[PDB]
Amino acid sequence: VFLVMYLFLQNFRATLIPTIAVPVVLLGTFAVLAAFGFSINTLTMFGMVL
Amino acid sequence: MLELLKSLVFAVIMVPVVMAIILGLIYGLGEVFNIFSGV
Image (cartoon, rainbow over all chains, first blue to last red; front, side, top):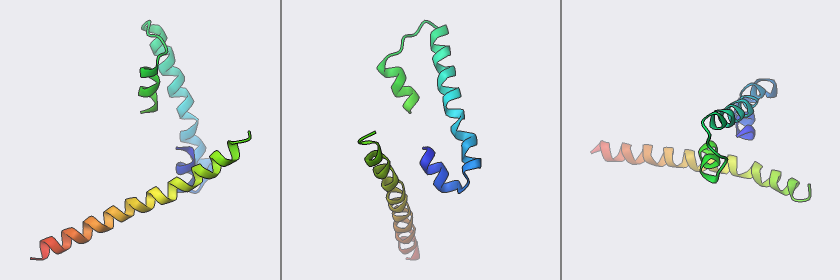
């Protein structure tokens, strides 16, 4: 995803903006799952990949 | 580290070719719609 955004926006200083949003969303989803008592399993990782 | 360079090189090649088949279907469907609607 990072490679295709960089190639199709032609500016690394601009493509760094959406890429660093990925870890924020992923870790926040992890925290949300922790708050609900859900456990890290293959289905949740498939959902994040999607 | 060993297979990392090969993984990067492989990652570079899908994106242009997949984009290429994407244009391929857009072109083909456009032309097929043009000929179908021409009648």
